[PDB]
Image 1 (cartoon, rainbow, N blue to C red):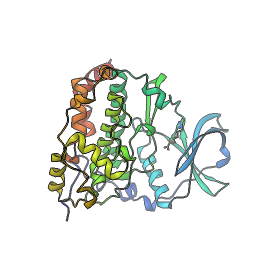
Image 2 (tube, rainbow, N blue to C red; image 1 turned 60 degrees about the vertical axis):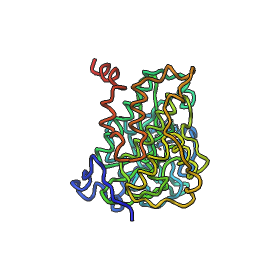
Image 3 (cartoon, protein in one colour; image 1 turned 120 degrees about the vertical axis):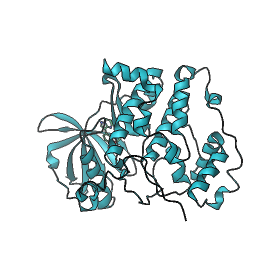
Image 4 (cartoon, rainbow, N blue to C red; image 1 turned 90 degrees about the horizontal axis):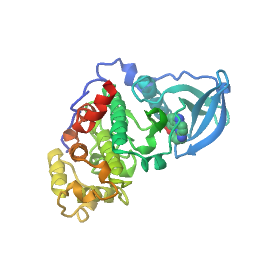
Length: 331
Ligand SMILES: O=C(O)c1ccc2cc1OCCOCCNc1ccn3ncc-2c3n1
């Protein structure tokens, strides 16, 4: 069958932890008092939850309440445990409280309020410096969570809150995140289509932190090239075709060979034969102000088929793309 794989970094971080850290099935939830919060207005809804601005009446603080739609106890425990383990880390959203919603007997997560600038509207205003700065801020959250033995597995613009006035960023929605254990076969049916790594699309289960770095590369491409989404597949199969038309089919088949991956036969007559394209075909008069040699070198080193060859978060932070930002933060 397939060749096994291990994270290059932070490989054994959870093995050295007490069992309780990662064994979320055993976690005992510390409930709080629902009557401390009053809902103010609805912010949005998804498959998994509805989100409200709210107020803590005991201190008149603004907070956000995420009312969970019914999922397994295990899934709720995993998100809670991860949020608690990561709490206080750089640019990690703060979980303030957990309450049992009386209406449905449903749990509600209570988060710190971030004054988020419009995500669709924000992108239209971002300069070259802003993209570098916010990318660096996301990398601080990813290096932290990876170093803590956790893969996010759903990195995308919707899950990055930006309070632009305060140059403040938070990585949110830890509902798909998981603990990394060497040898563990993970569920490939994760993340948003446009951000799925090749490992997911070819059904390679022994993946790791490096998944997040593919998703990040997809974000970077969409920002510097003004192309949202960058890899626009019609479904999961066509998503790999879209990637192959850019990264080329030679490297794809090399990856499949290296890991002895069994390719779904549906791929066979759709992948075809594609050259690896130069990034320069995506540069044009309206985006060129966002694109540098540095940006393209960095992007190239995130967007690799082989999960093992992508930059780590910590390596990415040392790339020349960030030298100006690093200098500015020291001062
Ligand atoms: O799932 C979480 O971990 C999550 C945590 C915090 C917030 C949202 C979350 O995800 C729901 C996304 O809904 C977007 C609604 N807009 C706003 C506006 C302001 N804030 N401040 C915090 C959040 C927020 N959401």
